[PDB]
Image (spheres, helix red, strand yellow):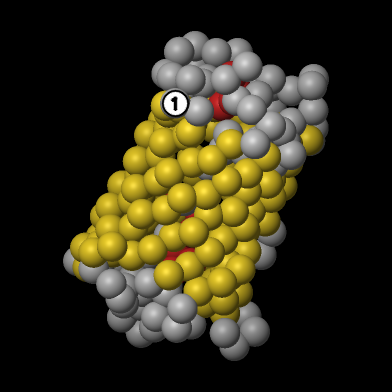
Amino acid sequence: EVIKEFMRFKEHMEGSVNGHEFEIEGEGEGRPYEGTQTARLKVTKGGPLPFAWDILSPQLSKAYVKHPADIPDYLKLSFPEGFKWERVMNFEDGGVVTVTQDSSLQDGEFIYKVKVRGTNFPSDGPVMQKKTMGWEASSERMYPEDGALKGEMKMRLRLKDGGHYDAEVKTTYMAKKPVQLPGAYKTDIKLDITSHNEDYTIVEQYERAEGRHS
């Protein structure tokens, strides 16, 4: 089995949000079959970012999702070659983030290359004003479509005030080879920022995800 009970990953992210370019590198580790992982991230160009780290967090690892045996683990099955994913997040106030990402397994470690593009966030919004405080747990609706695996969910970012700032998120996950697509199901996910420096140029995150029938 190429995917061991303990697996590390290395990741590179580049992109821009509202004209601000940046780059981030990260290294993480986790238990793929347990659906858990952590990562140490750092801004390597463009720091400090003038927008909420929260919008980048979900872009930083689907090989780490616990699945019952009766649900094909399409994304795990896709390794070592890997899979690619593209996403769009439509924020309630007009902000948008589109992402393209490549995942592969090279020499016992996952390699992630991510490109993010965010635009149209109001300068007085919670994103550009950094007033968000992490995501509430989500439940992504997974389903096979067009020979790919799709994911649909509304995500809620906590607002420093006490409210929430929402996003309708749509993701397409496509294995590099036609590994077995599963039927429709749901994945409960929770991502936590467990540590960060004041200006978020150094940040640590944890995420637990588990697939279950809907």
Look at 79% across and 32% down and name the residue there. 213
Look at 69% across and 20% down and name the residue there. 72
Give the vertical position of 57 relative to 177 (above or below): below
Residue 85 point in image, percent of width and height: 43, 35
Q: Is residue 173 left or right of residue 20?
A: right
Residue reaching furthest to the bottom? 161
- The quadrant in which residue 21 appears is bottom left
Look at 47% across and 34% down and name the residue there. 110
Residue type, mark 1 in image: Asp
Which residue is at the front of the view, 81 or 75? 81
- Does any portion of residue 127 appear in the rendered image? no
Q: Is residue 193 left or right of residue 34?
A: left
Residue 202 point in image, percent of width and height: 43, 70
Give the vertical position of 164 relative to 117 (above or below): below
Q: Quadrant of the image for the C terminus?
A: top right
Residue 155 point in image, percent of width and height: 59, 58
Which residue position holds label 1?
Answer: 107
Q: Quadrant of the image for the N terminus?
A: top right
| Secondary structure state at the residue bearing disc 1 | loop
Dot 1, crowdedness within 10 Å: few (<14), some or many (≥20)?
A: few
Residue 180 point in image, percent of width and height: 60, 13
Which residue is at the front of the view, 132 or 95? 132
Look at 45% across and 13% down and name the residue there. 177
Which residue is at the front of the view, 131 or 153? 131
- The quadrant in which residue 71 appears is top right
